[PDB]
Image (cartoon, grey):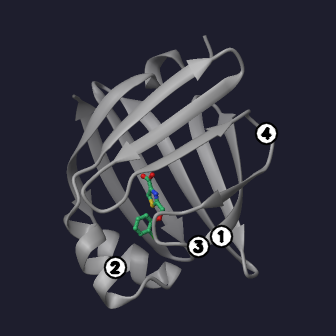
Amino acid sequence: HMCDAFVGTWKLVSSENFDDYMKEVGVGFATRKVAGMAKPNMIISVNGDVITIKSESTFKNTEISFILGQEFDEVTADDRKVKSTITLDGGVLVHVQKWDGKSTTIKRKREDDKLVVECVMKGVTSTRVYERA
Ligand SMILES: O=C(O)c1csc(COc2ccccc2Cl)n1
């Protein structure tokens, strides 16, 4: 019953500061423009201890499966090769990505009927809000 309130199909409904977050991460112009247009659907499922998060969009379909606290290799939608660890901290899914001596964190939280995604790199934060599909 780990992650129950996250499981489902979610659709992006608002974004703030994502272009700047992507700039901070190092994403180039053309990828920022096309990625920034996307309205992904995020599909979260759990089977035993394994959590799967899929994102589907016209930019780039992704899928990660993981066990909380157990590092895995991830190729991000912007083509970074990162080492990721996802944990639950006080009901918040915390997804840390390490690459080339850098770090970024993606937090996912249930707030009312929304799933709120906060992406932080150095001093730059982007907030992306999803609704049930
Ligand atoms: O909500 C997510 O899954 C999520 C937020 S940030 C991310 C990985 O980073 C990118 C993804 C697409 C374009 C540019 C970047 Cl930097 N995934």
- State the image coordinates of residue 108 (x, y, percent, origin top left): 48, 42
Mark 1 close to ligand 1, CB under 8 Å: no
Residue identified by numbered label 4 = 69
Q: Is mark 3 within 8 Å of ligand 1?
A: yes
- Residue where numbered disc 2 is placed: 31
| Near-viewer residue (98 or 93) | 98
Residue type (three-letter) at the residue carrying disc 1: Lys
| Mark-to-mark CA distance, 3 and 4 | 21 Å
Amino acid type at image mark 3: Arg
Can you tell me whether the CB of the residue at mark 2 lies under 8 Å from the nearest atom of ligand 1? yes
User: Which part of the image, by quadrant, shows the N terminus?
Assistant: top right
Determine which residue is flagged by label 1. 81
Alpha-carbon neighbours of circle 2 within 10 Å: few (<14), some, or many (≥20)?
some
Q: Which residue is mark 3?
A: 80
In primary-sequence order, the first of circles 3 and 4 is 4
The label number, if any, that marks residue 122 in the structure image = none
The yes-or-no answer for disc 4 within 8 Å of ligand 1 is no
Amino acid identity at mark 4: Gly
Q: Position of residue 55 (x, y in %)?
A: 39, 45
Horizontal and vertical percent position of residue 39: 22, 52
The crowd level at tag 4 (other Cα within 10 Å; few <14, some 14-19, many 20+) is: few
Residue sitting farthest toward the bottom: 29
The image quadrant where one finds the C terminus is: top left
C-alpha span from label 2 to label 1: 16 Å
Q: Is residue 17 visible?
A: no
Q: Residue at x 58, y 73 (%)?
A: 80
Picture coordinates of residue 45, whole percent (x, y): 50, 24
Q: What's the residue at 51%, 79% (across, down)?
A: 25
